[PDB]
Amino acid sequence: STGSATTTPIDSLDDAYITPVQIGTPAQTLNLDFDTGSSDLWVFSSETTASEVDGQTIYTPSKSTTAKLLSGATWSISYGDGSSSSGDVYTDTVSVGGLTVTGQAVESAKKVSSSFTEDSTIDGLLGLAFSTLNTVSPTQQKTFFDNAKASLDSPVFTADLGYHAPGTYNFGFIDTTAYTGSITYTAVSTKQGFWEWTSTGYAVGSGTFKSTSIDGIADTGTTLLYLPATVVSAYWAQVSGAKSSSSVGGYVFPCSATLPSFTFGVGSARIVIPGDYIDFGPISTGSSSCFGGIQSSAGIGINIFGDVALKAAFVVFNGATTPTLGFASK
Ligand SMILES: NCc1cnc2ccccc2c1
Ligand SMILES: NCc1cnc2ccccc2c1
């Protein structure tokens, strides 16, 4: 089997991407944030605290003839951005782009943090990291990909995120029309539950490539590119007037700037992030200070190849017995 679904930026900055997902019988379609950095499929629901729902579409399990309470199961998650959610668990039929899993754990939110309530565009998350990170207790549950894997034509999914434009998630096949040149594969460690890999180095604009190992995670559920402070200082030193602002919480730059590109290594291959991808716009409405898309990972404890980096590539999440990542230009 295969599936193919379009993913759409939630706003003009590509702050996140939503993908429609069918849950239940008859189908209830919710727009979920596909997150290769976490392993829970959770949704706004008919059980969510009413004051914490502001415009989201909700899953109502009582209206699904295939929904079953997973007796005694609860879940509770915190994300790197300080956001959180928790609740109870149903199993139900879940379809993405024509690919159907029966008996998927659908984690129904009873509580969500302020950031989730305040974002009307995201109805929940669909985790695509390894199932060892799933938070369901007392019986840990499998991701949508882990449940689908054995049925797929090939045990893979791909992320093709757009810059200010829709993109695609595919399951079970690699669309050879969707990228240029060849796919370079690189080793993955699953020891922390992430798609964790080692970049071979970086360049700033037309500068020389620096060969240096940068361990980090491929994370579709993080907006920005978080890298070591040495690398980030080198990038922003090429932008007149750029500075790290403790009050704003990262590097800012004059909105009148033209930003340089950023290149990262995948083995002997190179992925180029255009400068425009690194502009996240005014820090507040009408400001001439703009927020940078490359930020320090100091204090996060891991480097994160988020959407700023991934949207410059066609990315293969290879779930073979020994997982690997693939990157192509596009
Ligand atoms: N996309 C989910 C996510 C969020 N925040 C994180 C912070 C540190 C490490 C991994 C993280 C993964
Ligand atoms: N890194 C995963 C993640 C964390 N927090 C969020 C808050 C609001 C919307 C989407 C979010 C996604």
Image: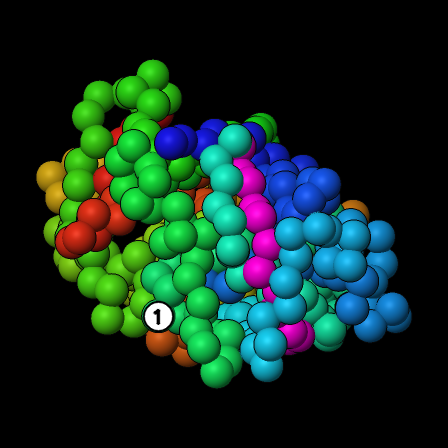
- Residue 266 seen by the camera: yes
Q: Residue at x 26, y 48 (%)?
A: 319
Q: Is 94 in the magenta? A: yes
Neighbor class of circle 1 (other Cα within 10 Å; few <14, some 14-19, many 20+) is some
Indicate how the structure is coloured in the image. Answer: rainbow
For the point 78% across and 52% down, the residue is 63
Image quarter in which the C terminus is found:
top left
User: Where does residue 118 sit, x and y in percent of width and height?
Assistant: 78, 61
The picture quadrant where one finds residue 10 is top right
Reading the image, the residue beneath label 1 is 132
* Residue nearer the viewer, 326 or 214: 326
Tell which of 165 and 144 is nearer to you: 144
Residue 43 placement (x, y as % from top left): 66, 59
Q: Residue at x 57, y 48 (%)?
A: 93
Residue furthest to the top in view is: 177
Q: Secondary structure at mark 1?
A: helix
The answer to whether residue 249 is left or right of residue 321 is: right
Q: Residue at x 58, y 71 (%)?
A: 70
Position of 268 with respect to 8 (left or right) is left
Mark 1 C-beta to ligand 1 under 8 Å: no
Residue 303, percent across and down? 34, 64
The reply to whether the magenta stretch includes residue 262 is: no
Left or right: 294, with 25 as reference point: left
- Where is the N terminus found, in terms of image quarters? top left
Looking at the image, is 159 positioned above or below residue 220?
above
Q: Quadrant of residue 133?
A: bottom left
From which residue to which does the magenta span run?
A: 86-97
Q: Main secondary structure of the magenta part?
A: strand
